[PDB]
Length: 187
RNA sequence: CUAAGAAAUUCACGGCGGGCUUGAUGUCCGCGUCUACCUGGUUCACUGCCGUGUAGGC
Image (spheres, rainbow, N blue to C red):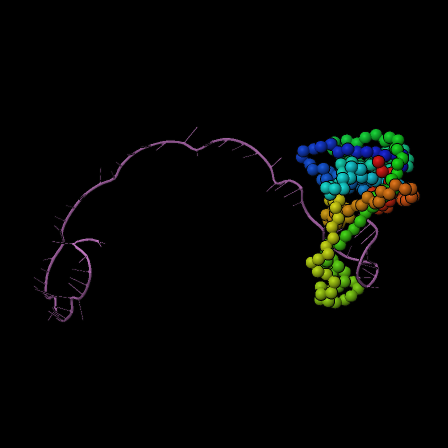
């Protein structure tokens, strides 16, 4: 979209940058659910996929002026000191097919044992013998702390930038989920 | 090529007993331990679509 807002976090000695990225993402999710718009894209530049750390930048995509003003205010609700955001400028158009989307993994076999026991396959000890073992525990690289709101606990969130094959531009949804679920123009 | 050249000391045994170390004593006075400080990077869970497996929500 043509309403991008790059945000560059100011270096603060008291706070690590991912600890503020989690608060920025939480305020963005809370005030993005609160509006009437449904598909508002979110992209993560400065990605650095060699040292396994998320970037210090963040951009939005919303095909309106009033909606992009609402989301310029939304991620900046109350903080006003740690963001140091920019101005909405006219975007270039390479669009190299890069789609950013959520992924999920299973590292707790006891939840699978609970689901096996108390929902479908009513047993006591067949569950612990049959499938699980202390092996094949997955992992995913970009972490977001993301404390919950509606009676929840601290749970990570993992995201993937897709294939950057520069051949064409396939149309997709702007956002599926909290922030991003589709393709965005990548710079 | 040596004050050279050689060589069986061998046997036995009862050290015994007796005894009052005694009393006496004033260690004793003094004292300033001060000063400063980010545990923090770090709670990958709960429960469900689902016969596995692998999609999703917060």
